[PDB]
Image (cartoon, rainbow over all chains, first blue to last red; front, side, top):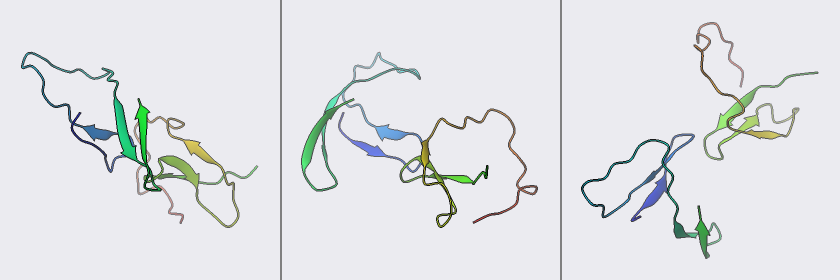
Length: 50
Length: 49
């Protein structure tokens, strides 16, 4: 994944994808799954899948 | 029944009612309103809050 962060838009957010073989492309509507760790508002680390 | 205006809140991403003092205290999700036609011209609309 590398990085993920929100956007000023109402809907979307931004995500990098990292090392990918050259012969690959993405179309709108594709679905990606990941298990990532984030920092809660209180300052405690959590884990989630989406 | 009185209808009160609802405005989008970019920080929380929900349609929250204006008129805080006297109004409904409910907030609705996005996708409640889906726009596919031409919008109302800005000249015709009246400004509130």
